[PDB]
Image (tube, coloured by chain):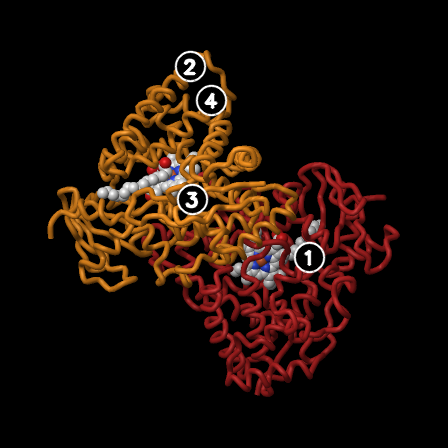
Chain colours: A red, B orange
Amino acid sequence: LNDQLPNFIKQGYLFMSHQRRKAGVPADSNCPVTFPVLGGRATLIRGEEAVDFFYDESKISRNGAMPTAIQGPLFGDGAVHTLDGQAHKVRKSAMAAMAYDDERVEAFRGFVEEEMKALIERWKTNPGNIYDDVAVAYGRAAFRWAGVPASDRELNKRATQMSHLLDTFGEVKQNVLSWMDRRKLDAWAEDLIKKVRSGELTVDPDSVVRHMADLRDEKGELVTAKLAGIELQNLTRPTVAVSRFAAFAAVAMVENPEWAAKVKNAVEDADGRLVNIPEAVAFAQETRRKYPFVPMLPAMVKEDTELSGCPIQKGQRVFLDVLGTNNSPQLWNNPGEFNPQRFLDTPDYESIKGFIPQGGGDVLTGHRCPGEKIAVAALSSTVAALSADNVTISQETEDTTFSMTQLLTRPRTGVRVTVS
Amino acid sequence: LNDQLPNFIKQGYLFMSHQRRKAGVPADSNCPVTFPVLGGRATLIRGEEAVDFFYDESKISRNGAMPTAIQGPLFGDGAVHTLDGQAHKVRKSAMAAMAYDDERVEAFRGFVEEEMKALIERWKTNPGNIYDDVAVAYGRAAFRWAGVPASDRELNKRATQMSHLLDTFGEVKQNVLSWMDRRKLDAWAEDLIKKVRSGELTVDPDSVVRHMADLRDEKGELVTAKLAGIELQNLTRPTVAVSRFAAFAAVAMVENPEWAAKVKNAVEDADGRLVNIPEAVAFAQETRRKYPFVPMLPAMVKEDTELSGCPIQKGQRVFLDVLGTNNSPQLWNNPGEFNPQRFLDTPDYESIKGFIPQGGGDVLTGHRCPGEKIAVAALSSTVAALSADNVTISQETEDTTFSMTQLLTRPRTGVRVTVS
Ligand code: HEM
Ligand code: HEM
Ligand SMILES: CCCCCCCCCCCCCCCC(=O)O
Ligand SMILES: CCCCCCCCCCCCCCCC(=O)O
């Protein structure tokens, strides 16, 4: 049983089933599978019992679990993702106060709406693809929502630099570029925070830029302008990432013309309202569940413990299959069908323990992604925006199909689109 | 407009509304009110803008703000409460390192659980009241958590002497007793610290008692053994104080039997454990929010400045309404309702700017209480303990009712309780 790192690069999102299959575990089963990867023992876990385990901070730490080749360029150095104990709780608290606050999310809903409404018209003259153009639109919204005091081009630059990062870090032949993207982005963010603290750059006192500039650590000292800038990115770039979900959502619409028209009816019955449309939210939630984005979640093991008969080791790495539980037939009724009706029946996605496309457990007391609201706020607005008639989504093979073996995958074209 | 010191003694916790009312200010309003008290100009402030102001250490000093009749017996002479500038930052750092460290809080959580679990069993044989008996239990836990090397009698003795202080100070006809209590406690603590420094009494090297005996100031010199004992009390006595919150919490249970049964279910699932129960924790925070303990906070003014049109001058004393802000309908959804559900929606109480029952600014860089963790840890453990069925809280008028004109008020009986 050699190291499974070559298999992970080869299989991509098929790696979870592959290790499951190559271990003799039945299909659709939740049985833990133990295998070596990255020169160490690892156990892939999947299921509701796995989610409760993954977030038991008494047995599961996170620092060092994500390899630096990924955490380095994507999340940045010293980010909230690599923190445990008190230092994390104080950092999440200050960050969930901006992305998880219902008031600030509703403010973002207005920013992302206006930016999208422009594109749908903007495309009519210079059409493009969803992934690239919506990434800029998402970045413009997140930056304006944060109070970033930069020009429009600078906003679009950083937006594409963040979208370029997400496209490159996952491919072994491009991870070197994602390091250059972060190096540039880290410098632009640090300079911004440095000028806010110096008064050269004055921002709104309640803005996200200000709360980042006045960020402090667990010992009560204010973080370095770099870290304050790294963490500002971790509140804007993960929004630019949603353009990949917008691409996936665009494919599902041309594949499900019935639900696409319901959204349309909804937005039509609301005259342009692209936000807070329960139908588009359900479509956005269904896209997050079915389509591949985050393959699995890595975590370290604090002490010798056990999960469902399979024993796991101290200092071991566990992996939570997020694609497998989100589509496990054990936990979902017909997971093969793209059906946003399941998220109109249960709108509170936090009650679904097995719905973990962006994390499980609690968001305030754990590492679960804050701003799933902000993500869906952006994602649902795009579903409503493309639900129109003047918009016709191109359906070439490179527009509708994506590779399951490619990490951070997406339709080749980025899902092209044209508007009349 | 005569001096308002007689009105404060007469009105108690209604004094803030009284000064608000006698100034023509509308009800529930946040308008500052200026009046003379203690032979000097004073301005009562209330609201989020007041909390940010009150802790702007660029405009507000604190030494001399608390009259010696209160600071003297309660906090002790030369305590961290009377410190400004650098000398405070050096002292808080060494003191918040014991009460604000999440690891040490979890250690105290086990002690307060063990001590509370005993009381409910003693009550079966010899029942009493919440205020007095839980004060001893809180003191027994806080002393053992700190590493106090004393017998059971001294632990029980100093604890009741500490609870006696809180009941006696603030009462004009009893403040003389709290001076005698402090003189006794100061001497017992000083003797303890002196024998720890001499090796006559050996304590755990990382215990709170040791970090107090090795306390140093801004001078780089270790504090006098007495002061190390005053500051040791300011990390054990304020825990004995929570028995007043436990008394208030006991009334709220017989007043809200639904949340009481909600906690009961919670503990039953936790297999007896009384700590880290999210339901009991939420119940504990609402008790701290609704019930009167700390009326207002006085502070000195460094330079002439302004708050919402009202000018305040140098050398003035400002008062931050903590009961008025914690129950202002402007800042809370139905603050008249006792609803721990509001603290399940937002568990991070430090993100709530208007929730200031034990301070409002930052705890590490300000004067905010560092024992809010330890406090709720103790208070919620009692909330879980009384949620059982064998526990019957007496509901006579002197058990359920407390005076709002009395300082450091509580039901007269202390909320009596009997268990089968
Ligand atoms: C494309 C949509 C997004 C996806 C797929 C996603 C996914 C994730 C995942 C899987 C985690 C780790 C959860 C865990 O550790 O259990 C995470 C963490 C995080 N996400 Fe997102 N996210 C998205 C959007 C956002 C947005 C819009 C924001 C805020 C602007 C955001 C902010 C964060 C933060 C701050 C963390 C760190 C949490 C912690 O480690 O304590 N994400 N994200
Ligand atoms: C009954 C519950 C408690 C209440 C109502 C309470 C209230 C307060 C208040 C209002 C302050 C001043 C905040 C400010 O200056 O803005 C304070 C300070 C302080 N408290 Fe408490 N407290 C409680 C429990 C505790 C506990 C359990 C501890 C630790 C064992 C503690 C230790 C301290 C210390 C050391 C300070 C000084 C902070 C400073 O002035 O820099 N308190 N408390
Ligand atoms: C062999 C290690 C694999 C472990 C897990 C695979 C890492 C892929 C996870 C993708 C993270 C995507 C985060 C989106 C938001 C952001 O821009 O930060
Ligand atoms: C006339 C001046 C009045 C100003 C405010 C009144 C002072 C009463 C506040 C009581 C403080 C109680 C603190 C409990 C915890 C501890 O033991 O430190």
Q: Amino acid at mark 1?
A: Glu
Kindly identify which residue carries mark 2: B195
Q: Are marks 2 and 1 on the same chain?
A: no
Q: Secondary structure at mark 4?
A: helix
Pointers 1 and 4 within a single chain: no
| Mark 4 nearby-residue class (10 Å; few <14, some 14–19, many ≥20) | few
Residue hosting label 3: B245
- Using residue B243 as the reference point, say whether residue B59 is left or right of it: left
Q: Would residue B414 be seen by someone viewing this image from the given angle? A: yes
Quarter of the picture holding the N terminus of chain A: top right
Q: Position of residue A2 (x, y in %)?
A: 83, 44
Task: Please report the residue visible at 24 percent of the width from the left and 51 percent of the height from the top.
Answer: B15
Mark 1 or mark 3, which is nearer to you?
3
Near mark 3 (Cα within 10 A), the count class, few <14, some 14-19 or many ≥20, is many
Residue A299 position in % (x across, y down): 67, 46
Q: Earlier in the sequence, mark 4 or mark 3?
A: 4
* Pointer 1 local density, CA inside 10 Å: few below 14, some 14–19, many at least 20: some
The spot of residue B381 in percent (x, y) is 53, 42
Q: How far separated are the C-alphas under marks 1 and 3?
A: 57 Å
Q: CA distance from mark 1 to mark 4?
A: 69 Å
Label 3 and label 2 in one chain: yes
Check residue A171 in the rendering and tell me which mark sits there, or answer none: 1
Is residue A74 left or right of A198 when viewed as pictured?
A: right
Residue type, numbered disc 4: Arg
Residue indicated by mark 4: B153
